[PDB]
Image (cartoon, rainbow, N blue to C red):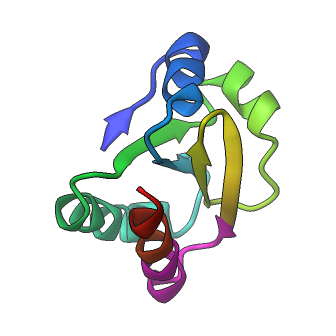
Amino acid sequence: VKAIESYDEWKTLTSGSDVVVVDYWATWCGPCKMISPHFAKLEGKFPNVKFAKVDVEEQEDIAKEAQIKAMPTFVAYKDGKVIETVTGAVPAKINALLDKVAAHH
């Protein structure tokens, strides 16, 4: 799962035609560490979807633009557009998001 390390990297990735799913997380987050391995398992299951993560405490400019309301939030992108947002760390919700994104890809 790619740790996104700059605003420019983030903009390049989310602007792509290939579908990307980003896990917005932080050290202040409760369940982020517990759900992260499941996200990594999904990355193995769905090799034609791009998986990425953003540490909002380290990436202020990304965080300001993403403007998340829940910690964590998973956001899917395609062609510079947010195509779906999933809040929280519920495995089934994240699995359902990937099913639908992977079909799109």
Task: Tell me if 43 is positioned left or right of 25 in this view.
Answer: left
Residue 89 part of the magenta-drawn span: yes
Above or below residue 11? Residue 82 is below
Above or below residue 58? Residue 42 is below
At a point 55% along the width and 49% down the height, the residue shown is: 25
At a point 52% along the width and 37% down the height, the residue shown is: 54
- Which of the two residues, 62 or 55, is positioned nearer the viewer here? 62
- Which of the two residues, 61 or 43, is positioned nearer the viewer here? 43
- Which of the two residues, 88 or 50, is positioned nearer the viewer here? 50
Quadrant location of the N terminus in the rendered image: top left
Estimate the x, y position of residue 94 in percent, counting from the top left: 49, 75
Task: Tell me if 75 is positioned left or right of 21 in this view.
Answer: right
At a point 49% along the width and 27% down the height, the residue shown is: 13
At a point 50% along the width and 35% down the height, the residue shown is: 17
Above or below residue 28? Residue 86 is below
Farthest residue, direction left: 44
Estimate the x, y position of residue 75 in percent, counting from the top left: 61, 54
The stretch in magenta equals 86-97
Estimate the x, y position of residue 4 in percent, counting from the top left: 45, 27
Above or below residue 29? Residue 80 is above
Task: Tell me if 104 is positioned left or right of 87 in this view.
Answer: left
Quadrant location of the C terminus in the rendered image: bottom left
Q: Quadrant of residue 8?
A: top right
Number of labels in the image equals 0
